[PDB]
Amino acid sequence: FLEHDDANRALMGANMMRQAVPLIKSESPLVGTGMEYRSAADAGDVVKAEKAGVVQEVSADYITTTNDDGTYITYRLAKFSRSNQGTSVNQKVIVAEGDRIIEGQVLADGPATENGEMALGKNLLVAFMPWEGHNYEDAIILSQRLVQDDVLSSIHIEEHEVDARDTKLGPEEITRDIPNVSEEVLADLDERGIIRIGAEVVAGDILVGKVTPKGETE
Amino acid sequence: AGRHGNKGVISKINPIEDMPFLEDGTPVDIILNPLAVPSRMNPGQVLEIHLGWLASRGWDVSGLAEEWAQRLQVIGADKVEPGTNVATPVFDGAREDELAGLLQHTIPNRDGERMVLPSGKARLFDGRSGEPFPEPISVGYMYIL
Amino acid sequence: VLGLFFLTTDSEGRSPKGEGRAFGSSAEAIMAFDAGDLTLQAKIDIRFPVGTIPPRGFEPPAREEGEPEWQQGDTFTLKTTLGRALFNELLPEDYPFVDYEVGKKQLSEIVNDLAERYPKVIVAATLDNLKAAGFFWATRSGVTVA
Amino acid sequence: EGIINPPIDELLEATDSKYSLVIYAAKRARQINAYYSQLGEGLLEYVGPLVDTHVHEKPLSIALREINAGLLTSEAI
Amino acid sequence: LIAQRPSLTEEVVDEFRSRFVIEPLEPGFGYTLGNSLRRTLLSSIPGAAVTSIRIDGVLHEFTTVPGVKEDVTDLILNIKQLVVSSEHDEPVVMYLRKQGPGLVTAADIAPPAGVEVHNPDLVLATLNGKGKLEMELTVERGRGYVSAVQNKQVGQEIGRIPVDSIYSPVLKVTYKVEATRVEQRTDFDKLIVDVETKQAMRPRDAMASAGKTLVELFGLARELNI
Amino acid sequence: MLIAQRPSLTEEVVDEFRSRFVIEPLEPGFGYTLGNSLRRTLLSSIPGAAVTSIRIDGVLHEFTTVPGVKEDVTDLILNIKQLVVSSEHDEPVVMYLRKQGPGLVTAADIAPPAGVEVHNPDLVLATLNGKGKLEMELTVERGRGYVSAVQNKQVGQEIGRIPVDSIYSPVLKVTYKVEATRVEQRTDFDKLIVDVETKQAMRPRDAMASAGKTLVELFGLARELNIDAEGID
């Protein structure tokens, strides 16, 4: 319904749909223009078949298909990888164990897509009414069902790095034996001073233990 | 934000029992100010919402012998199951008569009664006080980003 | 402002039930509204307790009596809707009764008069009351977009 | 039970200006806070809270309370 | 002016959906009682839910189990819809073990004594030939909704991941009023409350618990007076 | 499961009949249930007594002018409906008021029959000048809540009887507000404040106790379905 919207609001909406994060599981719009499939397939993050065949093996990490000419082609899927803005690029699967595949048919979804169709958000029940002033100046009131049912939530992956260098005084060491700290702080570190995979971490916690070799001592 | 330039920060995540709810106990998921839309001059979101509702509970149009009904029959949008996605191209969308007539002929949900009036608004209760709101409140499904 | 306007507007185009019936007090009018036989915008004859300042236009008229009377400090009956009674319940008791559609510009002159003639804490309390009741009655005003 | 708990119009009618009132209350708050940090030195120039005080209260609230109560004066040198 | 004590009558339309009728209510009063019942039913009703799990070979909810088409977060989503009942106040560990190709659902789970699943048709995941799923789902008892951040208590167990648990077993509550056929100008109203719950229990028990909570709070408001 | 803190109703009195009641912190979302249910069962479910019809001598239903009284019939109806009466008969009873000569007629001059009592004797009713000719008969009927003016073909039987609005409920107005309170680092607890103003006949706290009573045997209907437990104390 673009022809009903104002040109300024159309500008804002078009420039603002690019900021929509991909959610946990996405659903394609209940009402929306039919170009969404073409706008999702032409973007290359959706895994499409290079050749026509039949699915042989399906999993969360890969899809192995046997094409009709006889070759065996495996598509790997990026699961919980970091995009340039911090959002995940997790790719769901929509094909079954043994269904037929044609060329260009969508095998696996991408971030913010459902069934190969673009899905930038969720469809929610809406009522227009002033409600006790909490939707004032176009603010948002919403149910807790969008919190408990995991509707509007997103995985955010942040990368953060450090390097142990060779400065003038000596070589920086990645070590567990951090000085002037209690034992419980460094409890979750590895033998070489690395936080373990899947270790829940909070602000101020030790991620990787790097010590500078020495400083002018007075 | 929606797709029509409407945006806003979240001021309160209400409990489910505090949201206004429909005639079947279905709470609404998001409350929007109707003050914004006539000043922003983007009524299309409202249009979207009506068709969103029409795509939630499907419609049965056959033999109605009306202009919009015959257009939907020759197009193919005459028998639509509930929940199925609908498509309005960006300048060949569903016309006013089609939305009005489909809101007339929305499939019932329970007790053989349909829940949104042909005006596009539904009688909506209060989750806090419990007394029903005086005038019908426009409800439907908007795709929120 | 939309809520206060809806509260204080006239009964034009909206079906008035219980229009033109005397009420002993504003509490009885509220009870009738809760019963449902009286609408918010309906010209009713409502009595007001002692200490309620009558409107500025109420002074040239008076009750017909063979004895001297002064309706400036004591009880009086007024032909007004219930919404104006609630709106003046928001306003301070020393402020004269307002008997017109408020909207926005009349709200501006009311707030300017309040800031001119009243201390800061009273003004802050009255704008808080106006804010709260404006949101409350804008929720029940039935405004929506279809 | 807040910032506005001293009514401000009383302070203006007891001061006749607004900048005089704010620097007046600031000086009194500084005196009270210096008294609290005396550590038992017993300095004569620092006079404690003349109004009643809770277990913990900002010196400026106490200062405005003494200005409002009218039990304290100031003169220009 | 007439005094008649209200009476509640239950009729059933499905296995887990029923309508309760309270006829002699005072005018202008059915809506508020129905709303109090609905708000007590939707939020504060005790139940049981899975509060944490532990998948063998998985350290956090962002990996993938080797041999299932749904990642661990989708597994969290599918477990979060599993409705259960736990008699034990203490948490109970349920076991789900599946080998080989197939479709692991809630019917394939092993519920201990005192803990019962109620929707065995709920699909949990899929397995190909090299798929192998072993989960130890911790189930607890409570009311309302408790997020995953409030469900974590152990730090030494890396593999255990908490899930956000939805305890309330009531799907939707509605109320409706009419006018009684008795002829007075008061026009008393009957209240019909449609309660539909999940498979955890029949709506009669849920309405009983809501009535217990409401009568306890109102007796608190009563007995402290006079 | 178990409730950490138990609420406790406290009363802060401000007048002879006006009062305010504060509930110590309730569970999240339980403020509004208690507030509106208590307000509606307070304003409507408490039984009381009031007038239902009046009869003025030598007047007609279309004749709004009363002889000998400066106040019109509307002010007289308003003052009668503003009067408090208590009854125990449980059928409508006719109560008289007669006065001759000039002066002020109040509720003190009203003569009540046995079993019917008037709690407000000092409020003014009307004025008389010259010849009084004041003979009114008013019907007192025990009821519950609030009912407007209703006619039952009594105008056909006699022309002097006109119905009057009835205020049965002892409470005059109830206003509830639910705000937020913080204990044990959890801000989402509700404090409910119920300001109740009643008439001078009945004590407000007795009315609130009766409302809580009616709510107890009203929500005991759901209890007889099943004996189910809940986390208490």
Image (spheres, coloured by chain):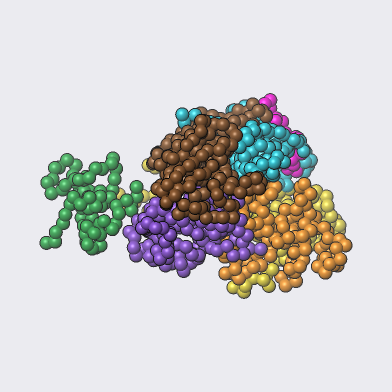
Chain colours: A yellow, B orange, C purple, D green, E cyan, F brown
Q: Quadrant of residue B144?
A: bottom right
Relative horizontal placement of residue A68, taking residue C39 as reference (left or right): right
Q: Front-most of F140 and F96?
A: F96
Tally the numbered discs. Answer: 0
Furthest residue to the front? F131
- Residue under the point 42% across and 64% down: C61
Relative horizontal placement of residue C14, taking residue A76 as reference (left or right): left
Q: Quadrant of residue E117?
A: top right
- Residue under the point 50% across and 44% down: F135
Is E113 colored magenta in this rendering? Answer: yes
Q: Quadrant of residue B83?
A: bottom right
Q: Position of residue B21 (x, y in %)?
A: 64, 49
Is D67 colored magenta in this rendering? Answer: no
Q: Is residue C66 visible?
A: yes
Q: Position of residue A179 (x, y in %)?
A: 39, 42
Please provide the residue range marked out in magenta: E104-126
Q: Front-most of F76 and F14?
A: F76
Furthest residue to the right? B63
Q: Is residue A181 above or below residue A30?
A: above
- Placement of the N terminus of chain E among the 4 image quadrants: top right
Q: Front-most of C17 and A2?
A: C17
Q: Is residue E79 visible?
A: no
- Residue under the point 24% across and 59% down: D13
Q: Position of residue B104 (x, y in %)?
A: 77, 60
- Residue under the point 65% across and 52% down: B124
Q: Is residue A27 above or below residue B39?
A: above
Q: Position of residue E102 (x, y in %)?
A: 79, 40
